[PDB]
Amino acid sequence: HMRHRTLSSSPALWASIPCPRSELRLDLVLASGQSFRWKEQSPAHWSGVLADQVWTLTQTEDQLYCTVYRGDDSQVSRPTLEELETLHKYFQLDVSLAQLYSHWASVDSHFQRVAQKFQGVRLLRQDPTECLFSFICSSNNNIARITGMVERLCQAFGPRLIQLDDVTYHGFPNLHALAGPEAETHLRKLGLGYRARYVRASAKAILEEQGGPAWLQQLRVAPYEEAHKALCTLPGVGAKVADCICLMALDKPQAVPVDVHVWQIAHRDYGWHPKTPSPLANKELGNFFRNLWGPYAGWAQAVLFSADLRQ
Ligand SMILES: Nc1nc(NC2CCCCC2)c2c[nH]nc2n1
Ligand code: NI
């Protein structure tokens, strides 16, 4: 009944945003461990759900093309002005990435070389809730298995939006849906394992202890270090997961999430060793990168991480 659109098939329902290739590369961003909700269903066409709506994104050299699926048995059309603002904010396109690239490049010869090939790696501005529970699922895991866990979780707990081909799209569940007495048992059936406990517990915690999703909005305006400590009170959320959320959902560009993977890069590519792995050592490494790259150190880190995935 409903199929995945392409730019050739139905170009009437698309709309463009002026966006250079050097500012954004969909294929280096959408499935590079930031969001787990985007899939290249057809070549160069990334479909995914964003704010209880489905999008398909494709780009050229200088233009970013996008179409929307409402899915309320209503008359189809192009993306509105407000829907384009949502996508503008999502990619944080007011921030020049070219100027940031050159800024980092001036004080880092290693970044200079990697920045040659891998342009247009930027940070998405995600919903806190979606980001929070996605990154709780990330512990001792990989992008492939995380993507599945998040998809199944949304199917079980989140509301249906639309079906395109054989892909049924669900929005991300609210906290109440994940806090229920059966939630852990269901999530274990879906294969999350121990992460099922942390998911339910954290949803339940934000509700009762922190007073619902407004708390996450408060953290978004709170200073980085205050937001980080508050997140670390949640079950299954430590320094690494907290930094991810800070960087990707709470607008803390200086947040540098450190795990064994970042240790590996830091050591191999910068020859870094702790002067003063461990919680203490991980914190020093985050300070190191902030000292080196400055207040958008988290954005620079994404370029390396994204570059490190692609051989
Ligand atoms: N799944 C996943 N994702 C990560 N995020 C990176 C890409 C986006 C910017 C921050 C780093 C991870 C970092 N360490 N382990 C990660 N796992
Ligand atoms: Ni060494």
Image (tube, rainbow, N blue to C red):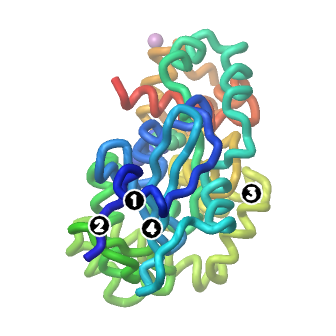
For marks 2 and 3 on the same chain, the one whose residue lies earlier in the sequence: 2
Residue 251 in the image: x percent, y percent?
Answer: 70, 52
Amino acid type for the residue under numbered disc 1: Ser
User: At x 51% / y 80%, what residue is drawn?
Assistant: 175
For marks 4 and 3 on the same chain, the one whose residue lies earlier in the sequence: 4
> In 3D space, how far apart are the residues under numbered discs 4 and 2 (Cα atoms)?
12 Å
Residue of label 1: 10
Residue of label 2: 3
For marks 4 and 1 on the same chain, the one whose residue lies earlier in the sequence: 1
Amino acid type for the residue under numbered disc 4: Val
- Seen in the picture, residue 19 relative to 276 is either above or below; the reply is below
Residue of label 4: 54
**Element at label 1:** loop
Say which mark, if any, is on residue 91. Answer: none
For marks 4 and 2 on the same chain, the one whose residue lies earlier in the sequence: 2
Left or right of residue 94: residue 1: left
Instruction: For label 3, count other residues whose C-alpha is less than 10 Å away and answer few (under 14), some (14-19) or many (20+).
Output: few
Instruction: For label 2, count other residues whose C-alpha is less than 10 Å away and answer few (under 14), some (14-19) or many (20+).
Output: few
